[PDB]
Image 1 (cartoon, one colour):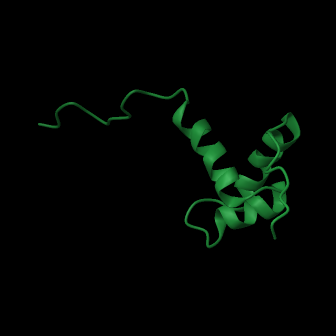
Image 2: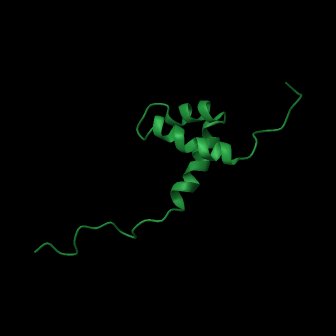
Image 3: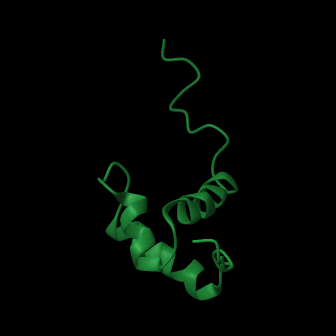
Amino acid sequence: GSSGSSGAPEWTEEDLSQLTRSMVKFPGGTPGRWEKIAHELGRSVTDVTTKAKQLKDSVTCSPGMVSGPSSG
């Protein structure tokens, strides 16, 4: 179709707050994870994963969760 329209809308507290809820319903390894979270949030797979990935990248956790420098 020649005619075209805008793409996908930005992220809003609503969409940013819902994601956390969906992520729980569809954890990692699950078949169609992003495919399910998107249908729930109302966005496109890439649209979601592309957003979540940013959240997983910028986080606050130990620089290296290690057990010990030397056993023996």
